Amino acid sequence: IRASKRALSVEPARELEKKGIKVIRLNIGDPVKFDFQPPEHMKEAYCKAIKEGHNYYGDSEGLPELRKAIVEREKRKNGVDITPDDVRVTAAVTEALQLIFGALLDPGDEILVPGPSYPPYTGLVKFYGGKPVEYRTIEEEDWQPDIDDIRKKITDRTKAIAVINPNNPTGALYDKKTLEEILNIAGEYEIPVISDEIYDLMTYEGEHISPGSLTKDVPVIVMNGLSKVYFATGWRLGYMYFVDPENKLSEVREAIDRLARIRLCPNTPAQFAAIAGLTGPMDYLKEYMKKLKERRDYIYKRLNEIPGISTTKPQGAFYIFPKIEVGPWKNDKEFVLDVLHNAHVLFVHGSGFGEYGAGHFRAVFLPPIEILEEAMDRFEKFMKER
Amino acid sequence: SIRASKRALSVEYPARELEKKGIKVIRLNIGDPVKFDFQPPEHMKEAYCKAIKEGHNYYGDSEGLPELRKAIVEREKRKNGVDITPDDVRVTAAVTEALQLIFGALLDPGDEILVPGPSYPPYTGLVKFYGGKPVEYRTIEEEDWQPDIDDIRKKITDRTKAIAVINPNNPTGALYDKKTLEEILNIAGEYEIPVISDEIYDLMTYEGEHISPGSLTKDVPVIVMNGLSKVYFATGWRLGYMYFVDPENKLSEVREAIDRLARIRLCPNTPAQFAAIAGLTGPMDYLKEYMKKLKERRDYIYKRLNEIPGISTTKPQGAFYIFPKIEVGPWKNDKEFVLDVLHNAHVLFVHGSGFGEYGAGHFRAVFLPPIEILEEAMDRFEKFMKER
Amino acid sequence: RASKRALSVEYAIRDVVLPARELEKKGIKVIRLNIGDPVKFDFQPPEHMKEAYCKAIKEGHNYYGDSEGLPELRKAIVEREKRKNGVDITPDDVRVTAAVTEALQLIFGALLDPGDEILVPGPSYPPYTGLVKFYGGKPVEYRTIEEEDWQPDIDDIRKKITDRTKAIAVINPNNPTGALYDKKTLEEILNIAGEYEIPVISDEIYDLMTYEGEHISPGSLTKDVPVIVMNGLSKVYFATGWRLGYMYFVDPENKLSEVREAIDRLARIRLCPNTPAQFAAIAGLTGPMDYLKEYMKKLKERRDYIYKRLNEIPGISTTKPQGAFYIFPKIEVGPWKNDKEFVLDVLHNAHVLFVHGSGFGEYGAGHFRAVFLPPIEILEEAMDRFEKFMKER
Amino acid sequence: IRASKRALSVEPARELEKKGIKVIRLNIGDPVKFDFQPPEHMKEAYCKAIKEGHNYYGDSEGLPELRKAIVEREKRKNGVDITPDDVRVTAAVTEALQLIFGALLDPGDEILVPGPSYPPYTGLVKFYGGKPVEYRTIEEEDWQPDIDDIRKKITDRTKAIAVINPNNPTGALYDKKTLEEILNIAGEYEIPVISDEIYDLMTYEGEHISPGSLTKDVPVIVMNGLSKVYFATGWRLGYMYFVDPENKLSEVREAIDRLARIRLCPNTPAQFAAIAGLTGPMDYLKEYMKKLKERRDYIYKRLNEIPGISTTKPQGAFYIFPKIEVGPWKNDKEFVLDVLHNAHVLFVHGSGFGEYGAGHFRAVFLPPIEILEEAMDRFEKFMKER
């Protein structure tokens, strides 16, 4: 029994932890594994939904009331002119991507993705028979897209340009210029922009801008959800919406609807929790952002005062992506294993985020300053020796 | 101009207009018990809420919580006598996701999957979505919709990658006997292909007991799928699981592919897995009270349908569907019949040809509503039938 | 910075000619069975066509002709197609083109918006693919069945047709398979076209190049459906280098009036096809077809011979071609991972050049194409080396 | 069944001829329709090629011996440093253009063309999804390009500047000053010049200068053929070559080659005739130019002695482009039809050559003086009366 070709093409610390060694894990982008939880009013709504009997299959498009709530939130934030019929509730951004790529992709079709890349995008495009094509982002510009690289990498087989902003793994925040220019290129070639907006409100200085706000003709597919901004990773709930005044995506939307129907629906009670998060008080976020900004400032400061390491200052999300300027290691994979075994600190090897990630590593600044301080002291010691 | 995926566009799957005009319609078309007088049991609800309050709101292992995988192992030993380990078990976002993972990991373009006829539509669309060909094997109404073994023998080709068994069955309510299951295993063994067993309706039986092919296999690798949607009345929780009866690891590459796919999609819902632990390890008392109401509703609709001239049906042995035959009438097909019943009798059925060619000349109805609603629906339908 | 669409234009069939030139540089002689050009072998356009060509030049017929083609040529086509195909057309239904190649550029150019589909056979003829894609169209390949000597799979056409399909291309007789389509498939293709209200495009360049069976044009068979027929001098008249052909419309209700007007505008900006060659064309079309009898005898013996030699080699099986001058054998067993690898190894060792089957799309994978254009003497030499190579492998 | 968008965008005397009225046709630029034929040695090579069996498909690049002959001829006339590999044989200048526009144009890309314009440029740029942008040429300067207008009209979407020299419809001959200034602009904006040189040797006073001779850095694509200078319009044969020391066209050449391969090849025997024309005696041309100059001088003299009409003296090709100074007509179209119905003389209306051609007409001076005399006598009489 041989597995499918498509499925096969889809691409240590436990041995330490089983001995009783505590490794500082800076590899995991899940805020809920640290001092973060979904706000009380979201927990209450979820639990009230269950008890009140909202345990049935919902409409495949998602609950009308949640779709209404998404409209108002996106109008307030992004000024986009959308209706509930422009919105689809999904099982997180993960399922958004699945539906979108499933509906867009024929064999050998291409999607432009940033490099350094977010690995689930690469696996998903490959699985749906497509070819993911990394466009360059520039470290010296705090990981802004290289628009000439986007221009060069477009072929007539390109079915979309994906924008992940704010960015994982770099923490970049794309400005109006970058976005306007990506939209112009996409408009020339008559293709949609997919905008991953999960880290939305998770910015440190200066607001996020959605390409949905800026487009005139170019259709944008915006994806968002509760995982990061609402600290509800294990609840698997999200959405997508279309900014498409000229109705250029009507065939694609119809394809998305067929795929959504056959899969039945996302979680029902979680969608009451989502209504609560979207229409509720944002005080919880103010407080989390404060401590997260402190943690950003701290790890940035610590990493830059270590000789042989440099890094940008992340403007969004909760990742920092340092460069290993000098050292004995053949590659970043070997480097990360060195730090694991000898400093008991776990990063992610940069090259796991594609070719533009090589010679880098990714760290999360989700742990409290005390944990970061210990991590950075050890890592500073490790680097001085090497 | 922006073209959709050829294969997405190929995924196939009015009463609302009547209700707009103030006309009240009885819906016998939706297989969702929670839309009626059925709820997930209290100890599962409490566990779900408790997981949330207690902070279990993070991404879990992509394979599923180790506690849930252990609870599944024990539950399947209890019911099916199978010896499996937690590492043979994968938690999924319902059976829907299980099917996506299995077909996604198994199918190359043009590979075949033998599925029952009448068919359950998700199987068809998913198999076609991955470039596969769904090949329908006959089931025999005269025999209460048991598989036609001879027909499975003839429909099998060198391109066939699995035989799907949906038992108890949607849309017919059939419960397959040891003989049919034993014979499907002999065929799968002969051609060296796995069996996929959909056991979502498991414990939802009236007379007779459900037997898993997993219990019966010797050499044949069996992939079993189940979950919370039906037996636990938690359709909206989107939680299920699959496991492998495969001591020789014949499906090792397939299993390895499933794991890669499971990894990229992160994990299914976290808190719902605690509710799952409470349902799997808990007593099944809640279900006894529910099966009583369902059996009397089964008995009632079956009686009512058979005493209507021009309509006949088998007696469902599992699930909550009945699949009657339209013997005589003016309609050109079962679609026309179902729209006509809707317009006039204000009862909503699903047309049999929606379940592929073996469902033609039939309609599916759920007997999920209380007797008072079923009585109302059957009175109007009977009047309608007299008239035509 | 070049056009994205121009840079994506593929032509894998020729993506094998470079390795062969390298061997010849080393003084190693190669037998070329990869090029469908009869004039490279012992075939020439008949004497009466040559003479008319030369006569046209000397008599001063060296100006721009009307963009639709010379009226005398359009009239000769009308009568020729009446005789062969029983079809009823006037000179205004005919357009002279710079070969079939240009007919295809005009038709696809005039018919296809980006995102439109065209149903084309698989294995496919590469220009169809390349031209459809250049215009933003999707070439959707329908199955043809080796077991039935490469006749269209009608069920597959029913499965692959959509509301976005603008036409069904029929290449008959067929390149690369040599298939000749029966009245059954032709009739059922017209039935599908009629149901979706789309035209049939019929490539009939190998028209009269048949061994047994009759070529039947879908133009002959149609009731309600518009048929665009393409033909020319290149193959049946052995004038590949003259670059002359034509198209015509079997469309009495003018369902294609808009498409036809568009073709005429495109024809107008390009000025015209070659003038003197059109007098040669008239000599071919109005003349006796005796010249073809002698050539067909040679081609039938070469067809018979290579089919015979190919099938007596273990690891190789093939259908018997009913038209054109190609054979498309299956590579049943061997060490190779794909047909490209197979084709290069044959070239290197047996010093015989085939075209890899996957250069004709996915339905061609595990196969290769050969021409039986060379004399028996050369084919014997070629098949001996290839048989030694296969035995060795 | 609808025709394509691109093919949609592509934009009388017979009724008189049917009565038996002989209109004098001064509207068609085909010299073979008058007292002109390709020289005998060209005819003989064509006919010999057919007899000797050169009737197969040639290489898509053209015959190596023809490419070698183009090289010698262009080295001798223009002093350019090219090899056979910088040369592509085409099905006339028309196919040169199709190949060059196909290979260059993404949707919305612009090509600068002269105004008054040669219409096929407009049609072909539009067909390939481009936008043709006319730059002004100046009547008082004998229709030399307006270099300020070129500077003004160029944008970041400009892909090439086309130069039609000697010019149709005006008969202008561009000089070194014009050419150097067009090259400077092209160099500044990093774009090639396309040079249409089909009327090359068809000059009356002073020699044609090719921008290929003048360039240092700027890539030039030169187009030429047998149609005009060798009076073989019906043979559909020509060529293009590249003057590009810095190899700035490497991608465009790849694209041209991809397009050339799939159309197979140009006519084979014509290429033997082309070798005979390019390397054979030019005696035939001396005699033809003599007669053409006499006809140029004649029509120029006649048109300038008709009150209400003015025109420049054409320095090249065989067209004259007179201004309709005064008269009752609303436009040049009305005028041309009036001249047809009442003088039985057929011109082309100037606005057929874009906006800068409004209020002009185009006449050919290919016919012998007796015919020109008769046409002018009728036209003089037509004008006096109106």
Image (cartoon, coloured by chain):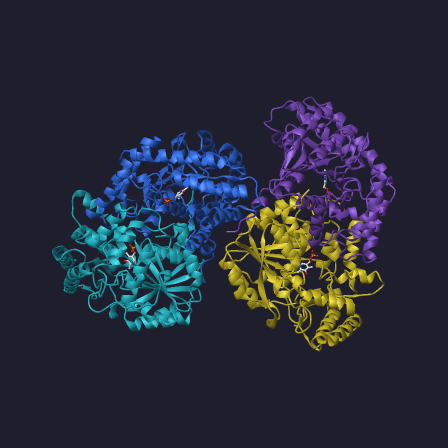
Chain colours: A yellow, B purple, C blue, D cyan
Name the quadrant containing residue A371.
Answer: bottom right
Asked if residue A294 shows in the view, the reply is: yes
Tag count in the figure?
Answer: 0
Q: Quadrant of the N terminus of chain D?
A: top left
Q: Is residue D51 left or right of residue A22?
A: left
Name the quadrant containing residue B109.
Answer: top right
Name the quadrant containing residue D200.
Answer: bottom left
Q: Is residue A52 left or right of residue A257?
A: right
Horizontal and vertical percent position of residue D231: 23, 55
Horizontal and vertical percent position of residue A212: 58, 60
Q: Nearer the viewer, residue C246 or C386?
A: C386
Q: Quadrant of the C terminus of chain D?
A: bottom left
Q: Nearer the viewer, residue A92 or C40?
A: C40
Relative to A376, say whether B152 is above or below: above
Horizontal and vertical percent position of residue C337: 57, 47
Horizontal and vertical percent position of residue A374: 79, 72
Point 38% across, 56% down: residue: D99
Point 58% across, 27% down: residue: B332
Q: Nearer the viewer, residue B142 or D35?
A: D35
Asked if residue D119 shows in the view, the reply is: no
